[PDB]
Image (tube, rainbow, N blue to C red):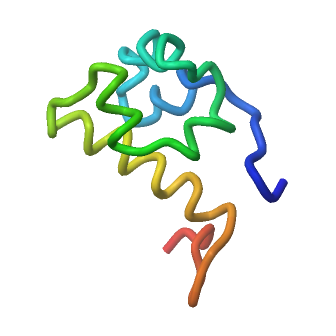
Amino acid sequence: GSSGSSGLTVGDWLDSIRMGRYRDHFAAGGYSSLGMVLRMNAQDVRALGITLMGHQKKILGSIQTMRAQLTSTQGSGPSSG
């Protein structure tokens, strides 16, 4: 998967960071899977309704890392240290 591989639901992932509560939102913003969530950003997330820095950071920060692994750059990524 070069573009983006899907496996779980916006809920499963979000749940990891205890943000699944916003899941419903993603589905409304046109995001029902991760394949698209990985290609999302503050611009997209914000639209979902999640603006609270306390949360926005989780979702976004949780995605930026979810995709960062798909393709590293100048170093390792998937590696769990």
Question: In this image, 51 relative to 71: left or right?
Answer: left
Percent x, y for residue 75?
Answer: 57, 87
Question: In this image, 73 relative to 22: left or right?
Answer: right
Percent x, y for residue 79?
Answer: 60, 73
Q: Quadrant of residue 7?
A: top right
Percent x, y for residue 45?
Answer: 37, 33
Image point 15% across, 39% down: which residue?
53
Q: In the picture shown, does residue 79 fall above or below 60?
A: below
Image point 67% across, 69% down: which residue?
71
In the picture, the quarter occupied by the N terminus is bottom right
Q: Quadrant of residue 47?
A: top left
Image point 27% across, 25% down: which residue?
50
Q: Quadrant of residue 77?
A: bottom right
66 or 49: which is nearer to us?
A: 49
16 or 60: which is nearer to us?
A: 60
Q: Residue furthest right?
A: 1
Percent x, y for residue 12?
Answer: 57, 25
Q: In the picture shown, does residue 60 fall above or below 12?
A: below
Number of disc labels? 0
Question: In this image, 43 relative to 28: left or right?
Answer: left
Image point 56% across, 64% down: which residue?
68
Q: Residue furthest left?
A: 53
Q: In the picture shown, does residue 24 fall above or below 13?
A: above
Q: Residue furthest bottom?
A: 74
